[PDB]
Length: 50
Length: 125
Ligand SMILES: *[C@@H]1O[C@H](CO)[C@@H](O)[C@H](O)[C@H]1NC(C)=O
Ligand SMILES: *[C@@H]1O[C@H](CO)[C@@H](O)[C@H](O)[C@H]1NC(C)=O
Image (cartoon, rainbow over all chains, first blue to last red; front, side, top):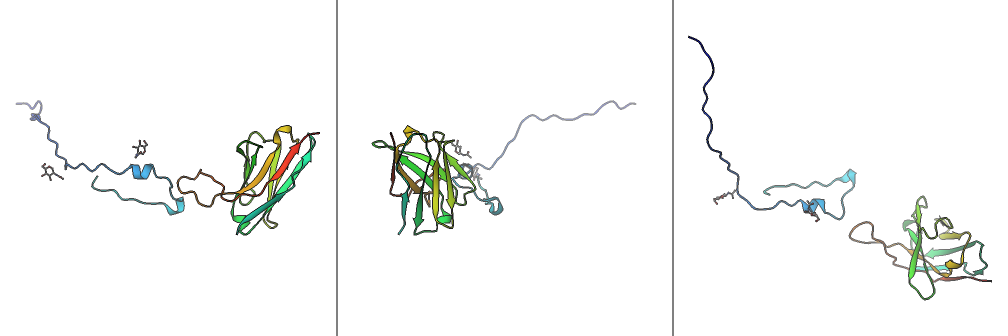
């Protein structure tokens, strides 16, 4: 009696589940800003729920 | 009250050099950049040059580049413009103008808030 290979079941379908929201993220307010800040006093902005 | 008075304009023959200046008063002179602007008789004005608030940096228009030189003196509250090899197309009423304090949007916008009086410079023979 000899051992040859392995047996494995293959998947059949694909499942994707993301939280459905539509708040487009505010990137323009940061990239298009008229005046930036000095490097020694850089400006931080948090981003969430986008 | 802020006011500027300039002097040194007059009639000269072609090929000479001039020296005129305006003396400021009523504000901290060292804290503001300055521009020279000329206006030909009957037409619109035209920008000429600019000097920084410490005199270490400057810029000029290409038309008068190589012939016009400016300078500053913080202590004496006077600023000079020197014309060399002056030509017939330099007849105008030169004003010395003060740089705009506040401009809001962007950093490349410039405007002149307070103007001078004017000196008539003409050339003939
Ligand atoms: C996803 O959609 C379902 C049904 O439309 C809704 O009940 C649920 O709140 C949505 N998820 C988010 C994060 O809005
Ligand atoms: C910023 O402005 C440009 C100008 O059209 C626009 O294309 C862009 O979507 C805006 N936002 C970002 C993040 O660049």
